[PDB]
Amino acid sequence: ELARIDLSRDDLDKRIGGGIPHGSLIIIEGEESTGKSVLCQRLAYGFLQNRYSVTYVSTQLTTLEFIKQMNSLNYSINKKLLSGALLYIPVYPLIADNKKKDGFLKKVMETRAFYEKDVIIFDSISALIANDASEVNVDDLMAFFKRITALKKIIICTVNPKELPESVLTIIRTSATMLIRTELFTFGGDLKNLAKILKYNMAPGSYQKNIVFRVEPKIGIAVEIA
Amino acid sequence: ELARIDLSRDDLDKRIGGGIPHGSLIIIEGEESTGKSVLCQRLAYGFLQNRYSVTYVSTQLTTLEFIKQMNSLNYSINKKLLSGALLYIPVYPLIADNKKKDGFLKKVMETRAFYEKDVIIFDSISALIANDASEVNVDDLMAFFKRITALKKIIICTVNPKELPESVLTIIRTSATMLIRTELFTFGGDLKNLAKILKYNMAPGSYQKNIVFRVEPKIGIAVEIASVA
Amino acid sequence: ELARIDLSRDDLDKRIGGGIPHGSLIIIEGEESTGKSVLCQRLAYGFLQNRYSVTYVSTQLTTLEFIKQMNSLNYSINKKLLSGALLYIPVYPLIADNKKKDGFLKKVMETRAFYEKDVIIFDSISALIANDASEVNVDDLMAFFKRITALKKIIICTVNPKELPESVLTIIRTSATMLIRTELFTFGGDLKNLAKILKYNMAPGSYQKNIVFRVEPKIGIAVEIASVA
């Protein structure tokens, strides 16, 4: 029941208790620049290196910009793209500041291709909900995700709280099997990221509640010790 | 007791129930062009990426042709060749002349080097039998393979049934721990491969009986997803 | 329990019983040119490929020379260096001047960066002790290593017995959880390394006591057959 994300360069696998449980819905919630995307990227790279397939749906980067970003963190994924191991889905209308309102959530729920992979990542699910133009609500979306995670797949969304009402956020949080909140904070001269695991159903072992890190060129996530 | 063949790009590991059991003798039987070789190639690449060693004995491709063929599927194995992780054995006399005759089976049974690896592939064992010139028979060869798989090694052979009488094929099939039959078929005017698992002793878990695939440039085996989530 | 060192190209993992136990202190003791370094290099490459992190502290090679040496063995570690997965520490004063003297052992015990990794390699610990100018003695160093291995880390040191008195060597040996002695010997006019496992606490399974190898271009450690299947 544990999906592995192990890399030589960090011990994030130990701090989440060994791996990510199959059937997890992970919500990563935090404001801009608090490290949500990089976290998704580290997790995606971990999975892909451990022979899992990943769908990565980005409301922010074209395929090109993603390849550069991953390459910049030394999480390069060119071979994985070529084989289809990594299915990257740029949401052009949200990338392009035309930003048009659309049945995003219907598309998300109805595109079979995404869910053939082991792991499906929506960075940002908050932008997709906030720009949806339909009677599909969040309870429906959450129910749908629960159905997919019941197949032992893993879903990971980022949420920026500043672009959704509290009413909606509270529902996403309840649905989460794993809820992580990201922030920035400063100690000594240093800005750092903190990822706090507010909730972790099926927690596969003892895990660290507060994970401090920084994002480093040509490393990615550098986790700070203890 | 399970040898892993996992790759990111497909879920073939799930469909064979998790992996290939140690001590397996896998027979892949089908006519020309039904995908036997590509299947051996996918398995070999999986084993190698999961830190197993492989010997691949080919009656069809020189080393050069093999490297290209592996590269064409994006199963490139250059580094594995250089380290000796992959030992590739072209059978030149059959490659140079389809019907050249010789003590192929004696060579197969006697070359130590092949059996130092975890997995040994003969593509085609049917060509090596059909062109053997000796008193070594199939029962002897099978008994020898059984002796090697008893050491926890894995052996994989392809068989073209056009090359051997039914009397012989029946023996091989009996000896197989895993028997897979390949064919081509067309649905929606598209041509596809089917690998059907007719027998699977020591099946390590629930597995798919019919595995449909197509061979795709720079992917290799694209396995058709049978269920829609 | 078991740290994996598996590579497709050899079966070292089977000969050490499956892997290296977490919390091991491995001492590799032998004279110059008996293969201690190459063995550390094989182990380091094994760990790195199996998703552990490694610190490699060398009294002999600059970073550049290490990259060339690794590349020469087909154990190339360029990407692991760039990510910090591999932290390589050249001890410049010993590299630049064979017998320069200093508080080496203070620097070793104090530098927290080294011990953030899963596996820490000192090649050579005997040079660092022999040229230390401090109070610090071997029992202290051993006690410090024991504390770190109690955190499930693995520590690996090479020892040239020509550099230290027998009094200090006997302490390191009794303190080792895994003790391996290396020598050269010649068979068929060919010179080979032998690594003998004199002691193996927490041995995770059946293991081979004698491991013969030669160092081969683009292979590294080429382990010889124990047994012919």
Image (cartoon, coloured by chain):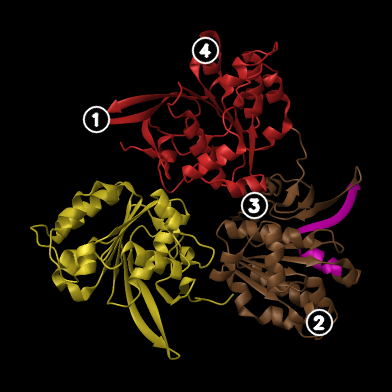
Chain colours: A red, B brown, C yellow
Mark 3, residue position: B19
Identify the residue at horizontal 90%, vertical 72% (top origin): B165
Q: Which residue range is magenta in the image?
A: B169-186
Which tag, 4 or 1, sits closer to the chain's start? 4
* Residue receiving disc 1: A188
> In the image, C219: left or right of B43?
left
Give the labeled residue for mark 4. A170
Q: Is residue A107 magenta?
A: no
Report the chain holding disc 3.
Answer: B
CB contact under 8 Å: marks 3 and 4:
no
Identified by mark 1, the residue type is Gly
**Residue B191 screen position, x and y as percent:** 87, 50
Q: Which residue is mark 2?
A: B132
Tell me the CA gap for discs 1 and 3: 51 Å
Question: SS of the residue at dot 4?
Answer: helix
On the same chain, marks 4 and 1? The answer is yes
